[PDB]
Length: 260
Image (cartoon, rainbow, N blue to C red; front, top):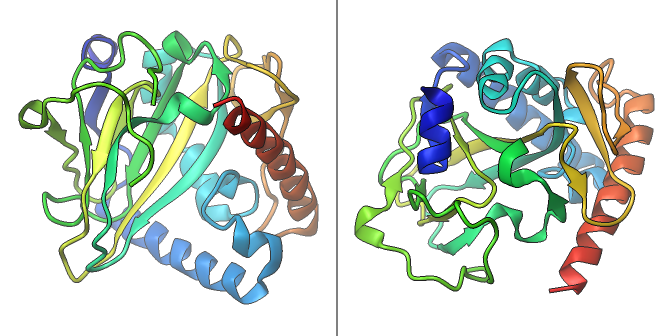
């Protein structure tokens, strides 16, 4: 029924992943990682929060391979899975900014996310009605990406029917890349930390340009050049593959953004 809920609503949550203790430990490792790349500066600091954290940081590598997440995603997308990107979405204490309703798919340049992709939104902290959580628009995914603070989907969203994504630390939400969502400001004294993972099957293909992804279930990488797991935090081989993979991805992003 998990797949049925996902396909009907365009999302499904909560699904269990990390324990509270694993969530807190992961958050500590994430914070340690952020400080470290900030001190190194350069390209790691610039791309600290996206799009390939899992290729250089052991804590991110561990989560995207977590069996509970992979099992949940497999029940939605099938047994052949790849990690296409990772994102840190952090809303610090008393951050007054808001994000308009929008869909993740707009600038990803992917073909086949309609049936063969899902974003896993892992709560490293609790998500509450007041700490800047995401809201979903149920059923807003059924026509794929739509035309678009950030830019906003050109459609009227019923705010009263929107669904606050409320999670215990360690739980996650899974939503369609065409799910319309918005996020409010964090009104609390504690930062809100979420780790987002884009899972795809080999039936997803880039609209244009060379692309890469990390095989996590199955043996088929489709059109994607294969990536590798980091042997250790900031291992030089991982850094070199990171530079290559991020450069490849940002070329794609730059290209789709140009075709607005």
